[PDB]
Length: 299
Length: 301
Ligand SMILES: *[C@H](O)[C@H](C[C@@H]1CCNC1=O)NC(=O)[C@H](CC(C)C)NC(=O)OC[C@H]1C[C@@H]1C1CCCCC1
Image 1 (cartoon, chains in turn green, red):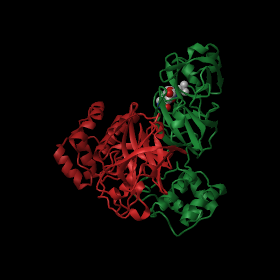
Image 2 (tube, protein in one colour):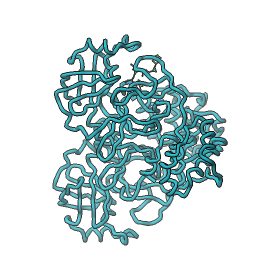
Image 3 (cartoon, rainbow over the protein chains, first blue to last red):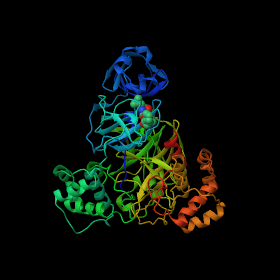
Image 4 (tube, chains in turn cyan, brown):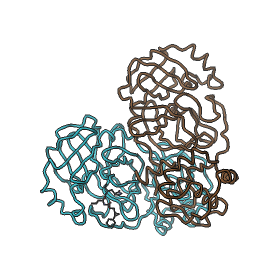
């Protein structure tokens, strides 16, 4: 079987706390003796339209920030801002801090999201960083400060902290240095993203997964050159396929004995014609949020 | 705009161990001072055919079971079989035991699966129990003893433990009392699931979700009796509704003001007339793996 699968979230759950300033409550990430959270916690309703964050922050003191780990209040003993993230220093070290790192993820890569409300983990699911630097998440009021991450041999690599929803229903946020993915800004305004394109290497990986699990109706005897495929992909707002993508797809091609460029010819046929009302792995749409690595770690 | 979203898995990660008999290792669930696992851990390859589980267990002693949390051995001090699960009493109460209960779910209900290998969690994902009592998992060799669960507040309701794969590639297993869902047995034989059907109650929940988000073209000005709807539904390979299904749609019916039986009438028209190229929540396909609880969780909670 083949399933969209999130990393086990326990190591991140032990880091989630609630952060409150004024009438605004969201989540923070508590690592060692620092809590990281979105800086817009310091805004009021009036501030959010055009917040001068440095000016709003100079007027705050440590005691204006209320941090709670469950029933326990953590004393804030220091605070600073790094881009769009606030760093609150507390007197307590988190005993549950995992081995971790902060990474900035590349578009087309996937990560797990731990959606939290009031410092309490609520759900976990897989997202991809879109080419237009949005993510198609599930985030409601109070979800800010929820984080996205990957796990590699007990090391948690944090890559995303949640800040906002766009009018189209997609989501935007920062890495853990507080820099946004994409052209977005943490102010209460309607923001549009650039035109979103489809992650072609991931669509190919998912077709290979549909073949492994016995689904073949889309394949064909034909083939294509890399450049000719990429001309058709760009026409249909698919990202171009690089030679590294082809290389990355090697293991999957070998396992199924289907040349990458033969799978490209199949995808070309799908783009030009369609599904014909049919489905692949249950879906009526081409799925582009599985990476080659994601697929390999499942067959 | 809906994601299949699992529950946070940490409270279950803290209960996973491995159980080995000879060279056969699967996963177990450590709650208080008991470890629960599939009884077929006591089988060799040649026993799998039609194992004599009672005979195989009589040859076993406490000191034949290797239970490990990580690389740390947990001493077994008692063993018993309950249906298709082994219960291994150990000398240490799990300090990470959550508040928990053991529940038997119904077809259509969803749950999170924490897929594990050698006692180590690998991934978490949502499954729906199909009307034919299979789930569409992603289970590899060594995954048996992985569990499915829901979390309500801080209480973990364990509802599934994994035992086997069927010829068609779907998966089968038991509740935490060892009772299989559906008509399967833990023998290494080709077993067939009944033909699957569409989970009507979840499709209705999906229509309610569509209405909540302002997508309501399919609502009509008619109603139906539950029996009339069930007889039509069966002709389209949809499950009949139970009284419990009607009741668990109550909150969404109240939220939208659309009576359950009126929504049934709208669904009946979709089944008889098709979608006519229209879409619902952006798709021409009716989704059947979001329960009414799942819908409320992503729309309002
Ligand atoms: C933080 O918890 C919250 C998470 C959002 C709320 C609903 N779903 C989410 O993911 N983030 C916000 O509320 C940000 C805060 C600003 C200061 C960055 N703003 C936001 O998400 O607004 C939602 C945009 C649709 C709204 C616009 C409509 C037109 C007027 C301006 C807002």
